[PDB]
Image (tube, chains in turn red, purple, cyan):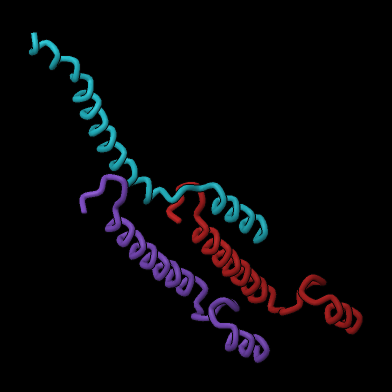
Length: 54
Length: 54
Length: 54
């Protein structure tokens, strides 16, 4: 398929790049905060237990 | 054979070119994801094994 | 996002042409049109031979 309107390989490459970007942002947060569970979004139950313990 | 309506050599060249593009896209996806087996389509057995092990 | 990409790829598979085939079909039809013009030009002159008999 030598189409000029659709480029599926670019779509797949963009999906992979977006996944890499998300992983990099997660590691950036985990470094600058020093916490693997810095908010309710990271893990709700363990974050709740930590808030109660603190 | 000096046909005006058909061109078998162009057909063979197009098949070879499509094969080359398929190999090139496989290498693109393999470099981008960083894994030689990134989905069940790559190889189902070791894919499932690695998924369970991970 | 992945579903939208898949739908766009399906539409592209459904309507888009394989332009590498028309890259050869175009030259084939141009040469065919030239041969057709020459053939019609030859056929138009059949009446001219009648003058020689008089």
